Structures are given as C-alpha cells and as structure tokens.
Length: 150
Image: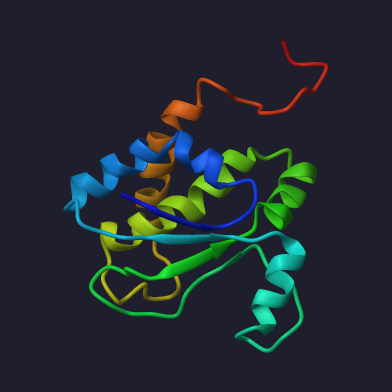
C-alpha cells in the first residue's frame, strides 16, 4: 500500500520489495500512505530549488511534516546514493531501502520527535526493517557484475 510517484530507478526496485514493506507497515498498523518521489540528481537539483530555492543535490529529500505517522511525500535520488555506493562499494539496495523504510520506520516508532535527528532506537529499528525488507533482495546481493567475487 505504498504510493509511487516520479521517475527513476527506484519504483521497479520498490515494486519488487513492495509487499515486503507492506508487511512492516501492516505490522505497525496497516493504514499508512508513503508517497515516494523518484528523482535523479538533476531532477532533484531543481526539485530542491523548487522548494528550498537552493541549487544543490543531496542524498535524499524529505518532506517537512510532523503528523501522527507521515502520510506525506518524500523524494529520493538513487543517483547520488549510488555515487556514494560506488566508492563505498555499498549496496544501493540497502542505501535505497533506508529511504524506503525511512517512511515506515518513521511511524514505526517515534511520532513527531526524532530527537537529535535520530537515536540508537531509530538506528537499530531502521536496520531491523532494512535487513527484514532486504531479507528478500538478500537473495540478490552485489547487484553488480564485479568480475571477482564468486
């Protein structure tokens, strides 16, 4: 029951582990609506100024709203994320999964608090759904060619 909007490698990846998230969301309560906006680097570059009025890319754009859960629209950009995963040889899937669960994990616990940005709770609670949701994609690690690891 997740809302997908925008465009860019993310939806197809979401639709893959869509139900996966529907589980965590369903667990918590099962009545949330997270609108994700897929936008590339440039797409976000402007989208940023479109509201922030500033010209600068970012990892992921979050929607300013403090309600029960969220029921808002957050924007993500796997362009910059991947760029980091490139050097950090990180799994764009996880890095993306974060922003994915970032919506659920949000209403998953804290409610209009997120004191000091995040806490040890949000960290582990975030890695919980991450590993849980990634538990599926896990069957497809690497996500890259890498003519080495066998």
